[PDB]
Length: 539
Image 1 (cartoon, rainbow, N blue to C red):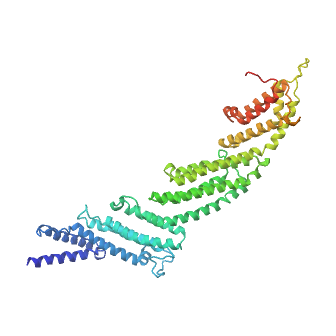
Image 2 (cartoon, rainbow, N blue to C red; image 1 turned 30 degrees about the horizontal axis):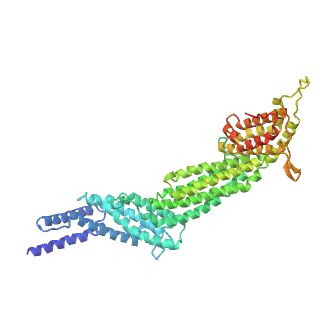
Image 3 (cartoon, rainbow, N blue to C red; image 1 turned 135 degrees about the vertical axis):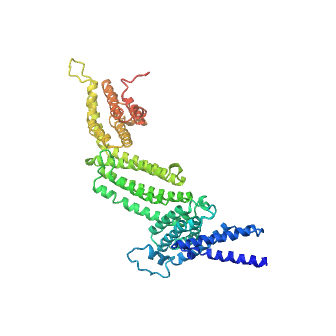
């Protein structure tokens, strides 16, 4: 009786749920009238459900929003299956303009191939068509429970989830085989990010971080990173040769370095820009990519440095004196634009291992500058020793002449200029060439090296330290031949003058460094043996 009735409702509720579990197919979006029937059909279902909630005062928990939702999920599962089984014909019919539109060629039907990634880009396009359909078409249609039934939001989650379990498995498959170009896995990783961020990422289920999807691609980018390191190496050779053939012209009068430096950092940056555009949302993975790119950056820059040191001495023949100055300028530039890269990879936020690979590089790079300046300063040494023995001769010719009115007598001040003159052609011709064409950090480094060499050579050449000879049983150092008082004064004043030329006002080394310089003190102590005539006891 009333039992005949309750069976009859269950049968009608059931019939409608069956209709709704294929809504896309049973109520195509193409038909406005048929979309009305879909609305009417959800209405009739809610009314039945509602009446059961009341008159069938017995609990009827199937609340209508849940029933429609579960029906919609079914239609979606079906849709996904239709889409996945007809990927090709659906895609070529509609989205392929296009040259060689023919199809249908590759059974086993492209979805998925392991030779090729094409099927997945097509399937992603078709997935979007549906989600957009469920947002644009069906959601307005089924507004009856806006708080609890957003068809488009459901379309996105279900379609993403279904697509995701397949893609996961397909990537595991390609991880074992790797038959595609990395550029292909790279483009897919990209197209998938767009899809996730565009439709899934703001969904409640997912709004809480962090997505699985990047891990599916992690191995394939690490491979692209490897291939990429090797392309960076080949770019670097013949980035220099273009520059070496061009003779290392500075790029501009403001611009202290040659073109090859901007090329290497442009290409290192383009590669970094690629990774940045994945917008990888898993920090453990992003730290992994950074770790590995830091290895690339290091081997590339070191290759840049190793390539000059190998060649540097060859440029130190004095005919082309600016060029060696530029390479140091270039090497300095590596140090600074690397810092700029280091920040772009996140600074302190950067993964520690990556941050350490780079700071260890920043150090090794700066040691290359040192060796490099030192080779340059030593490029002069022979000409310095010739300059210094030549100035020790003049000092030996210094003598007091005032004894007779002889008013042509040369003052200590004059005698000092005459002693310095043979080395002066260095200081004018060159130290005003250098600061003209040197990074500040670079010039400071070269001057500190030249200064060492001058105080070194003088401690050897004009001192003429006394020799050992046998004296009774054993070898003992002979007493120093003292300089004459005039000579003492000429040497002192000469030395102080030389220290000033390096100070260069403020332009050169600071007075503080020169005074403390152990090469100056080693020289001053050497002088002191010779200098006894004017040295004060009790300063």
